Amino acid sequence: MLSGLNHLTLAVSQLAPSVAFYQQLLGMTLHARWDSGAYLSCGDLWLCLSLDPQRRVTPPEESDYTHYAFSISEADFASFAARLEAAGVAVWKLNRSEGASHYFLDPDGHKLELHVGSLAQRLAACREQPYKGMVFFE
Amino acid sequence: MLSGLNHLTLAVSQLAPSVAFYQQLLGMTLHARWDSGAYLSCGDLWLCLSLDPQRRVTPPEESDYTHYAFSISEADFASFAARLEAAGVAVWKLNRSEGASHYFLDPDGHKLELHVGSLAQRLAACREQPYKGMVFFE
Ligand SMILES: O=c1[nH]n2cc(-c3n[nH]cc3[N+](=O)[O-])cnc2c1Br
Ligand SMILES: O=c1[nH]n2cc(-c3n[nH]cc3[N+](=O)[O-])cnc2c1Br
Ligand SMILES: [Mn+2]
Ligand SMILES: [Mn+2]
View 1 (spheres, helix red, strand yellow):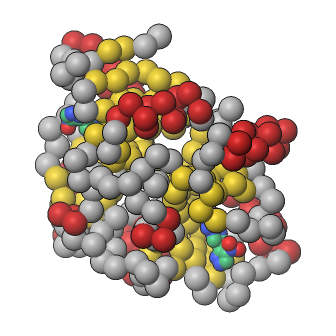
View 2 (cartoon, protein in one colour; view 1 turned 135 degrees about the horizontal axis):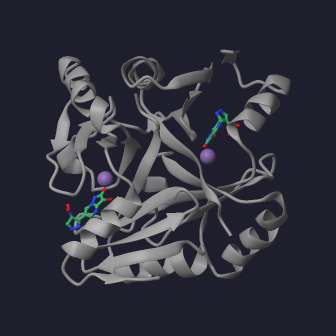
View 3 (cartoon, chains in turn brown, purple; view 1 turned 135 degrees about the vertical axis):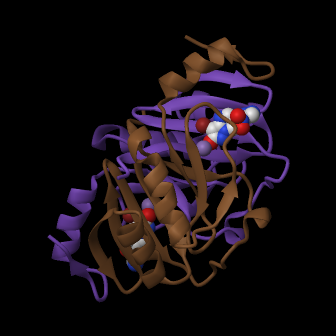
């Protein structure tokens, strides 16, 4: 029925710092901006920043595990993490899963992630060392 | 340089109803499931449902505008939106103007959307009727 993710929309408290975070720091392409939002792209990903007066800057301990992971090469992983570290971007988790992951927060506390690895690679690793109670479906 | 969305991870309060929602109702492909999570795919989208004791069933007034939109064809949009409402899936936003979108909630209150149209098509429509203060970047 569904063919993929059409877009991701993030509620932001301040449009300008969020645009700066995703365009200048993360390198996404800014396509349009208006008084209450912005459209950016990251590969095939359509990202909408939506100005929301209800959005507070949320500490990572006060939000659940819902998060959004962006693909990055193994070759770029270390330097991109250092770039984030130089900018003072907070880390909310340390990786314990297959593939390289860097868990960082956006200006409003949206939980983000850089990840090296596909679903196929994760499934193959899990076949070798399954999670508790793991069942596979073909 | 980030190349796209690697995966979307949703914190869920009850794994079984969430897996049933995304696999059975939304038709996504179930690849694996374990005691604390599940992996599904929707086209290129890698979806992880993660069992989280911190996740609450959240009414729509209690969360901000952050939401996740899935692509659907023009031919399938109307019948599937009717199927979701007939199945009792809650709607968290109704905009008559936005005929190509259907806003619905998952079992935990994650805000979802069916949308027909790409970013390029949205930009073209926006040039014809811009949002207030809109600026485009070629
Ligand atoms: O997910 C989305 N929400 N949204 C709101 C707007 C918006 N901002 N101001 C008014 C509107 N609107 O027309 O819904 C524009 N685009 C989007 C997307 Br894509
Ligand atoms: O974003 C994700 N978080 N996550 C946790 C797990 C998980 N379940 N149980 C233990 C873990 N873990 O390795 O952290 C598996 N996959 C994922 C993804 Br994809
Ligand atoms: Mn993740
Ligand atoms: Mn939307």
